[PDB]
Structure formats: C-alpha cells, structure tokens
Image: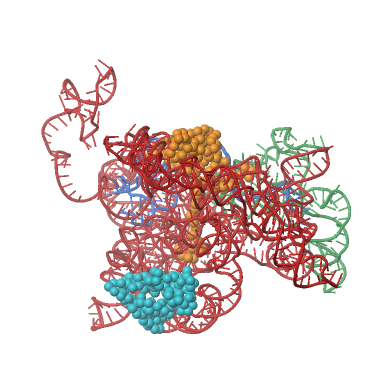
Chain colours: A cyan, B orange, C green, D red, E blue
Amino acid sequence: VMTDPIADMLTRIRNANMVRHEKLEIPASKLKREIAEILKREGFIRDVEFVEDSKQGIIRVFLKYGQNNERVITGLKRISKPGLRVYAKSNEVPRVLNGLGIAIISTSQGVLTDKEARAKQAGGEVLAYVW
Amino acid sequence: PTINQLIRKGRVSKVENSKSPALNKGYNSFKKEHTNVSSPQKRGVCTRVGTMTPKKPNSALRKYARVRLTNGIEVTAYIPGIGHNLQEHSVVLIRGGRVKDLPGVRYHIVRGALDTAGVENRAQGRSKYGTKKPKA
RNA sequence: AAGGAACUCGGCAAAAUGACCCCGUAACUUCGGGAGAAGGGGUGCUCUGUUAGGGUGCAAGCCCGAGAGAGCCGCAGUGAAUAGGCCCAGGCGACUGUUUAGCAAAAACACAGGUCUCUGCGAAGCCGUAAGGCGAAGUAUAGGGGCUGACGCCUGCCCGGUG
RNA sequence: CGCAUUAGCUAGUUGGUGAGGUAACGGCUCACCAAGGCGACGAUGCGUAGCCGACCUGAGAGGGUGAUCGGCCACACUGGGACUGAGACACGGCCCAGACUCCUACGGGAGGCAGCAGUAGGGAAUCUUCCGCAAUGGACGAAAGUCUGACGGAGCAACGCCGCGUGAGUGAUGAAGGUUUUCGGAUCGUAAAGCUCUGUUGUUAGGGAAGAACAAGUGCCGUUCGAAUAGGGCGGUACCUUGACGGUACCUAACCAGAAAGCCACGGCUAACUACGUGCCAGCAGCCGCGGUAAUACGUAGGUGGCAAGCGUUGUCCGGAAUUAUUGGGCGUAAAGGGCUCGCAGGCGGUUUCUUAAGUCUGAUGUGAAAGCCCCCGGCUCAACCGGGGAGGGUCAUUGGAAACUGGGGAACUUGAGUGCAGAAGAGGAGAGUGGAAUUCCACGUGUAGCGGUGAAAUGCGUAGAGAUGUGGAGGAACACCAGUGGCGAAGGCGACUCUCUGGUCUGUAACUGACGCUGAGGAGCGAAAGCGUGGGGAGCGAACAGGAUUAGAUACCCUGGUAGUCCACGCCGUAAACGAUGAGUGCUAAGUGUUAGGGGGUUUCCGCCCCUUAGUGCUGCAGCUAACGCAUUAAGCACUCCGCCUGGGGAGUACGGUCGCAAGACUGAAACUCAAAGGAAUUGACGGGGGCCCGCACAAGCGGUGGAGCAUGUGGUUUAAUUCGAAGCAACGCG
RNA sequence: CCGAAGGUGGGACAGAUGAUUGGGGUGAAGUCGUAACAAGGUAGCCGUAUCGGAAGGUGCGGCUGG
C-alpha cells in the first residue's frame, strides 16, 4: 500500500514538529535522502544522518528548535500527489511566502530547491512546500 | 472528492430557474409552438380586474389584475399606484416584479403603458407610476 | 350500370380472402403465444443451361430445378378447379372435450385445480334378503361423498336458530 | 454540448477481387464473395446549436455570449435535377413538382427582397421608398468611358460611448417667499437681486481646407522591339484636368445670461430628514418588513444625498457565492459512508540499479491572419476614436539537449503481500443425533369450592369435580447457572451437548516467493425481522378477530380467548435507527488503566510477581481537531490512495418511464408549485401526570360556618325616561 | 435504371384536450379526536405485516436519537 512515501515523510516531519520530537527514523529511499539533505543545507534541520542497512535503510532527522520554543519548520505540504502530478515550467516555478519559505522541485538536472531551479532555469516535478 | 472521481463524474452545476418565467417564452402564430424569447415586457389583454388580499400578518387590500398575454399565458399581475384606469379587456404592458404580499402575483403592470394611464396626483417618484412632469 | 349495408331483429344469405416463395408484423401476455396478426411484393412462356447446386451410376444417361440476366405475349400468368376474410373493443365460460338421437351446442355439464368431511382395512361408501362381490390383489401421497372450478390477488363478520 | 427516465446501433453497413464513375482516392456507384463494422473511452436515438477571431463578467481559474467588424460554412419561396462555364449543381440563370400572388381571349403564361430603401404582419422593440461613383475596390474595354444600393456619404433614434455645456468673479438687506420652530431663531444662503464680466455654445454675416493620388491627353529623356529617326510598348519627369458630402468640418467679427436639468432616493444594508394628511385603509417593498391617531419606511412639501442629458425600472449574463469548492467545500450529531462482502474494467504502486524517452522541462524553426485586449509613441482642439510599432496567447507540428520524477524494458532486494512449519482460542458455518428444567394437553388417584385476573372488577375456567397435588404419556419450541464494555464473523448475526464435513483469525519466527499489493463503478453473492409459494408443524406466544373492563367515545393501553405467523425443508423478497447514525487500505502522533488469546525475559523445578512485545477489546486522558457535544494510537488528529455520497425545507423518495418481483414492493428518480426558513450543538428560563429537599390553616386532626329559609347588602341579566359611572378568577361582587 | 413529390399501410415519439379521478399545496378563530414533544400521561422512532373515521393501534425484529 503506502501509495507515496514522500508525502509520508513530510507528515512524519510535521507530526514531529507539532509534538516537538527531536529525532525521526524514516525508511530512507534515495529521494528522501535528497529531500532531507536539502532541508539540512537550508537550516530547517539541525543535522540528518543515514543508516545503511539490509531491510531498506534508515534516515534519522534531528529537528531544529533554535530558540525558546520555536519550530523552524512550521509546516510541510506535498504538492504533486500521486493522482494529481504537478509540473512547473521555469517561468512558472513557485516562490513561497514570498521568499521566506521554499519548494522542493525535482527538475531535469537534480532534485533542486526553489532558488536553485530558478537560477538553473529548468522545471520539473513540484513535490514539496516547506514553510 | 478524488481527482479520478472528478474526472469521471464531474461537478454538476446547480440548476437556474428564472424568477419570472412567463416573460421567458414567446409564440409564433402559424408554427403553433412556444419559442424561448426571454423578453423584458409583454402586453396582453386583461381577462379579469378585481382586488384581493394578502395572507398573514400584513393585512391591506391589494389591487390584482389578471392578464392573458401575447404568448398565450394568463398571469395575475399587479397594478401598483393609487387608483387605476383599467377595465376588463384592457391592453396592459407587463414588467417582471414580484409582489411578496399577495401570493401568486409576480409581475407589475407598467404604469404609463399602452392603455394603463399614468396615476393621479403624484409628484414624487415621477417615472414610476407613469405621470408626466405636471406644471410649475 | 351507379351506389355501396341505405336491407335487416341481426351483414342471415351472398360476395370477398383463399396456393407457393420472399419481406414485414402491434396492444397485451401466464413469455409459450397473439401470428398465417396486420400490410405488402413475386409467381406464365422463351433463351442463356442436360446450369449454380444436389440423388443414382464406374462412366453414359436419367430425376430433382434455387437464383439471376436478357427478352416475348395477353385485360388477366396459383390465367381452370378448390385450397384463411381481416381488424378494434366488451359480457360469460380458462381452455381440448361433453350434452337434450329427432327444436335448445350454450354462459349449461365435464375439466386440471382448490377445499371440507368420512374412512385402521372383513375400511368408509355401494349392489344384493343373504351368500357373494365392487372398492381393490388398492391401504390416509389411499379410497368414497358434498361444494367450487385453470391462473393471478384475495376469500371479511355472525355458532343465536337448524344440522 | 445536454440527456442513460436514449444500451444496443448498422447491412453498401464492414472488408476483399473486378468494373464503372470522378479534377482526383474512396462502397462514391454496381456485380460476386466474406461476417464484418461502432459500442459504457457513451454507439445509436432524442433535444439544442452556424463555428471562430473575439465580447461581457471575474483577482484569476472560470462562467455566459457568438450583435457590429473579420475568416470559413450553409442557405436563396420548398424538394429534386442538370446545363453552361476555368470554377456553380448558380441569391437577382435554367428544367421539373408543391404552396402562394398575378394575368388570361381558359388554350396557357409570369413571379420569388434571407441585395439597398420601403410596406404589411408578429412583437416590449430597432431606421430613409436619399445624394454620388469625387475617393477605395470590383466587371468589361486598347483606352476614353459605362455599370456598381459594394463603397463613400447623407437622413432618423440619447441606442451606446466620449467630449463641451445650461454661466462666471464679487456679493449679508442672510431681502421677499417656502419649510420648520422649545417662536430667541434655524434653514433654503452668497444661493437671488447689487456691481463687474466672458461667449464655448445660441444667432447673424464674411472667408474657406485636407479628403486629389490620378486616369486619359500632350511634350521631353533613357530604353526594348522594329527594315528603319515610322509607330507602339516600359520607367522618370514636365504640364493640363477631376468633390456627392458641401460653402460641411473649420477660421474670423457682432449681440444678449439671454435659448438650455432633470431623474431617483433619504429606517438599516446605503450617502441622504423633518413637517402635514392618512390610520393595517390608501398604499410601499429587493430583503429585514412598514402603516391599526404621535408613520424620518405610505402620499405631499421643504430639505438633503446620489448621479447628471441623463436618471430610474425591467429582462438576461457574470460577480458577490469558498453556493459544484481544480484554484477553493464537505459526510459521528446540521444535507451527506453504499447493509455488507467477492471481485472485472479503471485508478493508484515498496526498495537498489542499468536503459529507454511516451509524460515533464529546455532550445531552435514554422505558425496561431487583419481588427480586438495589453505595452510604447503619434494625429484628431482633448477624449472617445484613429494610426504606427511591439507583445501576448497551442497539451500545435518538425527538430535538438536533460534524465530527477511518472511510465516502458531488463536485472537485483525484503520490509508490504503470500506460502511453509509450530502452537492457541473461538455462540464462525452447514448436516445428523441426544438431553434437562418448564409450559400446554391427556389418563388416573387425593379432595372440595373455588381458580384465574385486576388500579377496581368482570369475561373466562369450575361440583359434568376445576385450580392445588402425585404418577405416567404425547408434542413442540427456547437452550437457566457459565454469561463477561467475553469471543468469533464482512455485515446480517452466532449461546445445551456430541459427532460428520468445512471457513477465517491470532501468535513465534525464519524455510521459501519476491511487489505477487490497495481500492473498486458496473457485475456476482450474503443479507435481521415481517411478508410470499409449496409441503410439514403447532407447546407457549400472538397480529387479525371475539368477549369483558376503562372511557364522553376506547376500532387502544388493561384482562380473558385466539387465527396467520413465530418453527422446519427448499424457493422468492432484498428491506431496518441494516448504527460506531463514523467506507476500505496504510503509515505517523504523550500517557494511565482494566481485560481476551498469544510470545519472550529476571530468581524460583513451581506457585506466582515484575519487565517486555504482539493482535483484539473497554474507560479516563496531552498535543491536535471541532460550531459545540465531544473524538483522541479502536481518531472525529496529521497525511496519501481509491470508492460511495451531499449541495435549503416541502412537494417527495412522489409521479412517469424502465428493470427486478407470484405479490407486497424494491431500485432508479424528477417537475410544476410553494417557504424564508428547515436544521445542529449549546445557554437562560418556564413547564413535567420526572427525581430530591423544604415550607404555609395548604392537607390531615378538630371546632364553627356558608350553600337551604327570612331579611340586610353588593353584582350580573331584565325592565326601564334614567335605573349614572368605575371593579370583573385567585387579585370584581357589605368594593370606590 | 435512378429519381422529388404524392399514395397506401403498420408502428414509434411529442404537445394539447377529455366525463371522471387520485394524491399535493394554500386559505376567513369550521368539525372530530389529541398521535408526537415532559416518564407527553401506553417511551419514541426504523423496517415490515395487519386492522381502524382519523391522527393512529397491534404483532415481530432492531435502535437510543430514554
């Protein structure tokens, strides 16, 4: 079943925000590794680590509550659901909360972020809003 | 619902019914059929001019003329102003206006029309009720 | 001739259809029917052909003869004969049957069905005084008697009187 | 593009060979064969409709429109045909048939305004029977020219848009007069008049453009032809010509504020208020709703407000409306989870890697005409408008790059799924057999006068011996205690016991497979109870029905009887408040706590305690959700997939149609009409023939009365000339 | 030969209209009851059968929305 694992990792991060958990184990496909690597390098996460194993692998996420009680990640969303896929041209790439959030957009040269795909001027799947 | 369910059944849009349907048709004489003309006003000949009453708490006697039209339909229209010319077999031009008080009546007799004379002794609301600018 | 049911108790009688092949066919329906519904078309002869196609024969030759084209005659081609008239609605009876030989063929009987009641088998009922039988070499899914009549939906109230 | 309440539609239809025919390919037409073709991705049928560039609305997505202008189409009184011609099956051509109008000497003829004007009719409703070919096209001509209702103009209509107007500066006697007033005034208000002044427009009178370039005719020059400087073609000049609009736009001078403002509203939404008349009447209204003698809501006046040669009403679009929700809604209780399953099609698809390039992105090329929207400039006195220049708009075609994702193809993996092994539990199902209470009935003994039943009784049963009691027998149906928010099943549902056959689950894995999975319209099945058919069965109960009570009535509740049914076999129905009023799957997201079936551990061989983990089942609870109640790891949280369903209440789950059914009915399912609510959850009260507590001459316990009689007194009716008026259950009536 | 129209015929769809009829809605303080809302005076409702002037009653099963 499970029907798409990208939306499920985004809700797993969102529920870990609302509970204010500090760690997440996610069963770690390769696009999940690139999503959590992007969210690491954009400062939404403290750090992300990989556990390469036999079953399917584990990716562990360390959610960042930088100050007093401040969810750096406020909300996540999945745009292209498996049943309405979303594809944006390069002159239609969405900039979110106008600049203050971001959109994980997997174009033809790598799973890119918003600004990266805008400056590389290619478009593809539009697969997460991250606020 | 889901997108596949929206693809194979769609969103069915809500039905529109006109508030005044007897204007919303017409008639040609030799084709013997009942065309959709969507017209603002219709002249017809009075079949019965009486007066009758509303239903509940509001209680004051209304005006009530019944008119058969040029498309063929008899509707009870209303004669708005104070004191009216009309008889039976009177030529009447009808606009669409709902009279909430008297039930079953959903048109006005245009005052100032073909035979419905402008009302008597009126200076405020001149164009409604038909009367000319009198003199000064 | 013309008219055509104006006859009449009533289309009684008479007329009309009436064969073979093809097309097409309603309401209703118990799904079977209705139905040969209805309403139409073609039917001769001649040459293409002892044919296309079959039956028999080892072959010859004999039968059977769809379909087409061409054409020919007639007012008329199942040229005579004799071989449905049809449709719409209603009452009753479901129906096929039976019936007053010799006035009444029915809406009457009968019917499949339903129901009630009797009867333990030497049944009950029946014939006969009785023997003797029928029932029946049958045994309550059986056998008599009353009633109602396919099928569909149902069959209300009264046990006071008479049984 | 609307309907499935249109599901089956084709037969020259679907192919073949051959021929004909056509400008051409072709069942386009014909012969001969084959049984094809379209189909829930919606055939066919019915209804509607010219399509588009564009136009209106909207933040946009969209929704509606298809006027003008421009492209393609189809039509020419209706149907058919051909002719000629390059091109027609021809608007102002032909032949035929039909209807209509006309002429006729009765034999026969003519006609087609859906060309520009106009007429009649239909209608709420849309124009001149005008001037010109001057300009731009067309046709013909060698040309001049001719024809041109195309086109240029002109006329009518506020029909729309746009622009300028009806004056301006100064002005307090706040004049007269209106309206209002606590009569002090406030207001119409610097608004009139006073003074000063303009002339756009009004009018009179002069002057007068661009739109004109030309064509043709001359003369040159260059040049090609030529037998040649004839002569003609081609190009450049260099002249002479040409206006319907029209003495029109336009410019200039003269004169006078003189000619020029109305419509709607004023309770809220919604800017704008008073007065007089009316008195639930007249009337207003889009809604809330006004008006029943103090109406800012009706009618009028004053005033104010909005706009402005317009204004208001109507009719339709779109918005508002997140009110069809893709953007952008929902389903526990407001409308809404199919009763539940098995599953076809469809949709969706765990992981690693190679490859492909259909989707996706990107580049180049073509193209999406002109006008239009948009940008930038220009010209009309500005504006509308015109003009120039550009942009925009395609899931568009060809072509070239990318390879993350979706998909395709191959190889790998084990978590999801499933098989294997091992146990465990269960009212899981179906068939047969058996039991023990009790109930009824039957026979006999005991024995005597009641039993039964009720709020009270009565009907019933009973001296022909009942009820009670003892024994025996018949027969049917349900299975006390166990028994439990316990178990199993998809749901319905399943409780004695035993066997026969049989379904599923849970737990422990590691042996295997390696994505085999989820969901599922339509289909197929199960599906409580009642009901139906056939055959049995009948103990209790019990519709219907009867008697007795109650009662104003009592077709009821109560009582006494009692039919079908309840039961069984098979077949049909196919419905429930079929409920968790909560679709299925999966993952994530604090705890505490019982319990059901398992597993493992820390001492003990145990009993047993603790810890740990599953799957199911309860309660309380954090975050989160919600309108609230509440849900909360068994979600109503946070998500993804798929299905079903909702779009105010009624009419109405109705009617019609269809399918299914023996029937009863089921399923599908509107519309006219009608309302401004229907509804959920919660709050305050009031009430209850609901619970609790309490109190008072309220009840009881007493004592005396009133109601009866006589009179006094007050009140209703009635008599009246008047029997004055007021009070009218408690709370009027020896009351004022 | 094809062939428009016309003719005959049997069906299909659609609109009127039709004695009569059946349910529906709305209406001047009409008649009969009081079924529901409270334990609504027999808890109510759902499905189904049956009966009854009528709301309704009764049976069976289910539900709490006691």
Tell which of D534 and D447 is nearer to you. Answer: D534
Tell which of D370 and C77 is nearer to you. Answer: D370
Q: Position of residue D468 (x, y in %)?
A: 27, 51
Q: Is residue D598 left or right of residue C5?
A: left
Q: Quadrant of the C terminus of chain B?
A: top left
Q: Position of residue C39 (x, y in %)?
A: 72, 49
What residue is shown at x 53% (from left), y 40% (from top)?
A: B93
Q: Is residue D88 left or right of residue D534?
A: right
Q: Position of residue D400 (x, y in %)?
A: 57, 79
What residue is shown at x 43% (from left), y 74% (from top)?
A: A114
Q: Quadrant of the N terminus of chain B?
A: bottom left
D562 up-or-down from D606: above or below = above
C1 up-or-down from D524: above or below = above
Residue B63 visible in this rendered orientation of the protein? no
Residue D499 position by quadrant? bottom left
Residue B99 visible in this rendered orientation of the protein? yes
Tell which of D370 and B66 is nearer to you. Answer: D370
What residue is shown at x 48% (from left), y 71% (from top)?
A: A91
Tell which of A65 and D673 is nearer to you. Answer: A65
Q: Is residue E38 left or right of residue D35?
A: left
Residue D182 position by quadrant? top left
Q: Position of residue D524 (x, y in %)?
A: 51, 63
Figure label count: 0
What residue is shown at x 58% (from left), y 47% (from top)?
A: B35
Q: Is residue D36 left or right of residue C123?
A: right
